[PDB]
């Protein structure tokens, strides 16, 4: 019925940094060749969407943010072969073209068609499908899910199980997969190890889930908000520590509690100082530290290279190291088979029109993941 | 004949920073329990010994430096079980106690008894076996090989093949093992990969040897001294580049020549800026960069954590990651079986008494390894 036509719908537009989202009427153009128009069903509020509002994450404005979501294909442009109208799908903020050097490498996942390194906030063809008040509105990492309808490139969408609960599996579009993969795929947590997880929001909780699934014996959660500790323990943290309770630096405290440094540490916050602290708290000769948190745009950290010369391994990853199009469908299938849980991350559910309230909950420290329904 | 007695012999003592070594008479005490007194046969001049002179590497002075060497056991203290008088041995600047958490971990080699993290420059018992002009002289990483005789702890010595040529296998005590292991063990260079090696001294040449033995397809040598290029090519470099020949930063140049960044990069110099440049030139999603070079004491580098967040792996190692006492004897055995060559690193041979001349050759850029004979 709407196939091949402009759709007029509501979307949350961010017109300028540090302002509330504006629920407005936008026009969404029909999908061009190899493009997929999606009717959104659920979208999570991730800290990275708030980074766009705060200026932490820089991307051309005005913009329709949102990148963690699930929806139903409304229509497909010419040449699309991987999804059909009616299919449940999850948009991929990291594409999987399957032809670049990274897509062909066994460990790479940061596809070279990404819109993160040199952000333009467009479709792959350099143009936008969004218009508001007559003005073109940018996309966000080829996803833009804070809208009733969006249009993505075929390499930025994956078909998922037809029976999946989209108000839950939207978390596989970012939060869950990032945390879980960070532990299980990037760090490769080992059985019996000691892990330290800095930041106990949705991503940090999914890191804990992954460490516990990998058989870690000790999983130490670190947060300055102690209200985060109960849920952290629920999904696997054996201990939790608040840096504000101590008179000495947390890396010392953690080095002492792990009898010389942890096997695996994770930075899941987004601060330069906690990135260096997480590196330091892993065992100097064989420790591994993974950066997951997004740092303030263009800022450099300072660190002593002797931390690495002793033997430490330092790495970072986008989306838990998962090749997005190949893994999203398998993660949904595993969720359907009850291999992991997603309810522990969901603390609040709000209609899409209350998006600003959902961001207020995140910023106040009260929520983990707010799921917005359309 | 000398067993149980103080030995009077010549040693090169460093009384103060930035001065020539002073060839003096020293008194070497007999070995205490679990100690081994070694008659030196050959010692190489590594850049790290020059770092002690320049103040780059800090350790208590006055000191007997030198750590890359081979000699013959003169006598053993009570309780020594792993070596005997007359054995050929190689002193280990990284110990292998075999009991600490690092020694027992499969991938650790930075034994907790090392004298590097908090340098005291003494034997394991906190005292020195060296005296000069009535003053106690410090040890250097439990080795101190710029002396006709030295005393080391049993965990800092390995028994090697009785037929090995000590004027060649002394390089297994540092230079060769470090570079080689950095490629094959730490980085785990893969067949068909592209490697970039910053610094073409003896350790950088050894890194090339390990990349070639791992089957790398391309091995790009980087050095501001183009006189280093011929030998680099001889041992495996497919191309060599001098940063001074270009108008743009070397990481750009290397990213362009590897069509998007190399698989494995190695910092084998000891500069903060080349450590970051080496990291950057490795492929942003799956690249691996290994720091081998020793940076100026207590200085921090500055870097953007986005270099890691895209997927890069950054690591460092001491002694190429080898568990010292288990690996040195195998390396010598491999060398005896012609599994690798050591002659390409040796450009000059001088009597011990010309140690200052040997340091002048290194500092002028003329040599790779000068072997000193006793
Ligand atoms: N690499 C990726 O692919 C990817 C994917 C998703 C999110 N992220 C990033 O991961 C981070 C975490 O995301 P989230 O959605 O879980 O966010 P969140 O805001 O829900 O969680 C962060 C947690 O850090 C805690 N915290 C803040 N400052 C702290 C400090 N100084 N010390 C200790 N704890 C502190 C907060 O109390 C909070 O619980 C963000 O930076 C987000 O942008 C990266
Ligand atoms: N990690 C360890 O276990 C270990 C063991 C041995 C040596 N090291 C360290 O490794 C480094 C190399 O040792 P070496 O004995 O081979 O030293 P070296 O001095 O023989 O070689 C260093 C090479 O780097 C080159 N170089 C200098 N500045 C440069 C720049 N700006 N750009 C590019 N190239 C530059 C020089 O021309 C030289 O050929 C030293 O810092 C040494 O202390 C570490
Ligand atoms: C390291 C920067 C990654 C930014 C990505 C934005 C959407 S997802 O939350 C992570
Ligand atoms: C990272 C510092 C290691 C310094 C050690 C001194 C002797 S060997 O050259 C390496
Ligand atoms: Zn790709
Ligand atoms: Zn996200
Ligand atoms: Zn050395
Ligand atoms: Zn040990």
Image (cartoon, coloured by chain):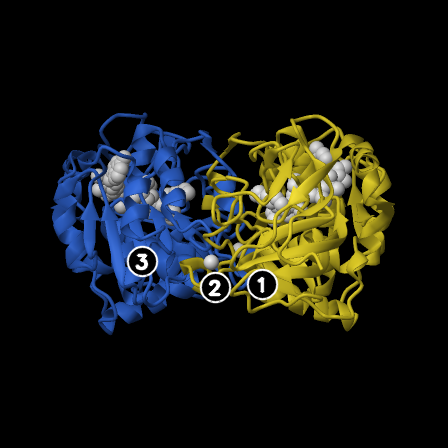
Chain colours: A yellow, B blue
Secondary structure found at label 2: loop
- Asked if residue B233 shows in the view, the reply is yes
Residue A18 location in percent, x, y? 69, 26
- The answer to which image quadrant residue B128 occupies is top left
Residue B157 location in percent, x, y? 39, 57
Identify the residue under disc 2: A98
Q: Residues within 10 Å of mark 1 (few under 14, many from 20)?
A: many
Chain identity of mark 3: B
| Marks 2 and 1, how far apart at CA | 9 Å
| Marks 2 and 3, how far apart at CA | 21 Å
Residue A223 location in percent, x, y? 76, 39
Left or right? Give the position of B284 relative to A176: left
Left or right? Give the position of B17 relative to A339: left
Identify the residue under disc 1: A325
Q: Which mark is first along the chain, 1 or 2? A: 2
Front in this rendered view, residue A336 or B136 = A336
Q: Say yes or no: labels 2 and 3 on the same chain.
A: no
Left or right? Give the position of A40 relative to B133: right
Q: Which residue shows up at 59% across the image and 42% down it? A: A139
Secondary structure found at label 3: strand
- The answer to which image quadrant residue A35 occupies is bottom right
Q: Are marks 2 and 1 in contact (CB under 8 Å)?
A: yes
Chain identity of mark 1: A
- The answer to which image quadrant residue A234 occupies is bottom right
Residue B86: assigned label: none
Q: Which residue shows up at 55% across the image and 69% down it? A: A81
Secondary structure found at label 1: helix
| Marks 1 and 3, how far apart at CA | 27 Å
Q: Quadrant of the N terminus of chain B?
A: bottom left
């Amino acid at each position: 019925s709407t196939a091949g036509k402009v759709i007029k719908c509501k979307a949350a537009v961010l017109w300028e940094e540090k302002k509330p989202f504006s629920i407005e009427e936008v026009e969404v153009a029909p999908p061009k060749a190899h493009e997929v128009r999606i009717k959104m069903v659920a979208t999570g509020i991730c800290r990275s969407d708030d980074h766009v509002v705060s200026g932490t994450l820089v991307t051309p404005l005005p913009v329709i943010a949102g990148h963690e979501a699930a929806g139903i294909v409304e229509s497909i442009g010419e040449g699309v072969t991987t999804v059909r109208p009616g299919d449940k799908v999850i948009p991929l903020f990291t594409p999987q073209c399957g032809k670049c050097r990274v897509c062909k490498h066994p460990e790479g996942n940061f596809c070279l068609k990404n819109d993160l390194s040199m952000p333009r906030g467009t479709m792959q063809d350099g143009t936008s499908r969004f218009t508001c008040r007559g003005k073109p509105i940018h996309h966000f990492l080829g996803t833009s899910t804070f809208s009733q309808y969006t249009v993505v490139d075929e390499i930025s969408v994956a078909k998922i199980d037809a029976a999946s609960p989209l108000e839950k599996v939207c978390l596989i579009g970012c939060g869950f997969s990032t945390g879980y993969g960070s532990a299980v795929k990037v760090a490769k947590v080992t059985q019996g190890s000691t892990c330290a997880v800095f930041g106990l929001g949705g991503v940090g909780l999914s890191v804990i889930m992954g460490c516990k699934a990998a058989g870690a014996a000790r999983i130490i959660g670190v947060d300055i908000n102690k209200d985060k500790f109960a849920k952290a323990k629920e999904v696997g943290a054996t201990e939790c520590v608040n840096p504000q309770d101590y008179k000495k630096p947390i890396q010392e405290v953690l080095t002492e509690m792990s009898n010389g440094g942890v096997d695996f540490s994770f930075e899941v916050i987004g601060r330069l100082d906690t990135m260096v602290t997480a590196l330091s708290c892993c065992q100097e000769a064989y420790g591994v530290s993974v950066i997951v948190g997004v740092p303030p745009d263009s800022q450099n950290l300072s660190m002593n290279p002797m931390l690495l010369l002793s033997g430490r391994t330092w790495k970072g990853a986008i989306f838990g190291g998962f090749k997005s199009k190949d893994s999203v469908p398998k993660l949904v299938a595993d969720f359907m088979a009850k291999k992991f849980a997603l309810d522990p991350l969901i603390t609040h559910v709000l209609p899409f029109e209350k998006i600003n309230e959902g961001f207020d909950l995140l910023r106040s420290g009260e929520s983990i993941r707010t799921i917005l329904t359309f």
